[PDB]
Image: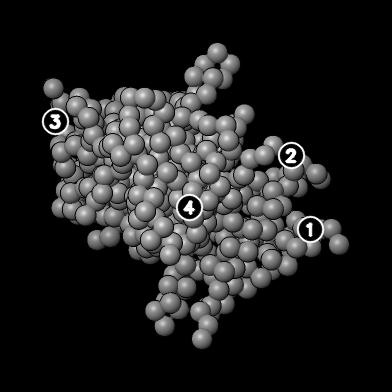
Amino acid sequence: EVQFLRTDDEVVLQCSATVLKEQLKLCLAAEGFGNCLCFLEPTSNAQNVPPDLAICCFTLEQSLSVRALQEMLAGHRTLLYGHAILLRHAHSRMYLSCLKLAFDVGLQEDATGEACWWTMHPASKQRSEGEKVRVGDDLILVSVSSERYLHLSTLQVDASFMQTLWNMNPICSCCEEGYVTGGHVLRLFHGMDECLTISAADSDDQRRLVYYEGGAVCTHARSLWRLEPLRISWSGSHLRWGQPLRIRHVTTGRYLALTEDQGLVVVDACKAHTKATSFCFRVSKEKLDTRDVEGMGPPEIKYGESLCFVQHVASGLWLTYAALKKKAILHQEGHMDDALFLTRCQQEESQAARMIHSTAGLYNQFIKGLDSFSPALPIEAVILSLQDLIGYFEPPSEQSKLRSLRNRQSLFQEEGMLSLVLNCIDRLNVYTWKEIVNLLYELLASLIRGN
């Protein structure tokens, strides 16, 4: 069978390279908040190390002919060769755009210019202009603004006159309303609001243990998880009962796992190999006595309505509580009330949780280099990130926007972002550099203002 790409479907842009007598596949990736420059995310070693897929997803917002494009400048449509496409970054909501003799490629805030448009062209004589773009086709993408090819420079991405072959691999298409798909950020609730979570920032358990917890946590970022099937293509398809998948903690970026040494913990991406890190949802605890569809597949698990037992695949152990804040363990029998229900996180909350992840990771790297000087400091990155967050926490000038602001502030504060910003300040103030110090203080005020 064959399938086509349509507008509003989500995709990864994939290219290939030969690395040390081994073939490597890389996806187009960008963070999109201060760090607007695109980079390559290797997806070949997924069985051992899960890729950072969240920021590789692009939505095909628009697909227009050359004549239709010029008109705009002055349901779901199928992609045709010769059409110009508009690629909206899922996380940042910004657009892929054209920034020796090669122009950079990054994210731009507005789809107004020609810079964010790319025409699709066949890689061989197998396809013709005006024909449907198929899934699995090798294609060439040229920038409308610069007339240059989106290209893998040698691993980096830029726009040049040297061309490279891309695969626009489908992440998801139209999904059934209310059904859980891969790549979704959600909460796992147990029975009285009590959800699966890890500890708050700067706890003694090193943020590596899992708990069932009630109260305010159900509205905090630390209880957010992303479901990640063992696929790249159609990783955003409907989740099935018994389907193996990884469960990623959003703010921390670590993976739910079973270890021989500690049991149920949350481990770093570098140590999250499928055997330790694969879970699945089960209808019941009965012994399973009994194929991967290309596409969205059958819808099986409903948000809210479906009750699911979580099982670690390799061991067969059940996710359960040790007999309000109960520790989560993996156990041979578990409890009769182990069934969880799932609730989808909304855009603002999930976006903020990923912003926390990226911010914490960058500022931790910035702190690390200083303990060494007691690898260039990410000065340009830190400044831009700081500048972005100040605007992010900027009080609206000229009540609903005030409620949103206070929720954003709360989300960051509960993820230990105040002490983290302080932790940078105290390290920089040791020396009597000047750009960041002022920006860090300004963000500090922005996080506090109106509390």
Which residue does the numbered mark 4 point to in the structure image? Answer: 116
- Tell me which residue sits at (55%, 13%) in the image: 21
**Residue at image x 52%, y 39%?**
150
In whole angstroms, how far apart are the C-alphas of marks 2 and 1? 16 Å
Query: What secondary structure is found at the residue carrying circle 4?
Result: helix
Which of the two labelled residues, at mark 2 and mark 4, occupies the earlier sequence position? 4
* Cα–Cα span, label 2 and label 4: 33 Å
Q: Earlier in the sequence, mark 1 or mark 3?
A: 3
Number of other residues with Cα within 10 Å of mark 3, as a class: few under 14, some 14 to 19, many 20 or more: few
The quarter holding residue 232 reads top left
Q: Which residue is mark 2?
A: 375
Give the alpha-carbon distance from disc 2 to disc 3, as whole Å. Answer: 53 Å
- Amino acid at pointer 3: Glu
Mark 3 lies on residue:
286
- In this rendering, would 438 be left or right of 239? right
Numbered label tally: 4
What amino acid type should be assigned to the residue bearing mark 2?
Answer: Pro
How many residues crowd mark 4 within 10 Å: few (<14), some (14–19), many (20+)?
Answer: many
Q: Nearer the viewer, mark 2 or mark 3?
A: 2
Q: Amino acid at mark 1?
A: Trp
Which kind of residue does numbered mark 4 sit on?
Cys
Image x and y of residue 361, in percent? 58, 48
Q: Residues within 10 Å of mark 1 (few under 14, many from 20)?
A: few
Q: Is residue 271 visible?
A: no
Q: Mark 1 and mark 4: span between their CA atoms?
A: 34 Å
Residue topped by disc 1: 433
Does the image show residue 161? yes
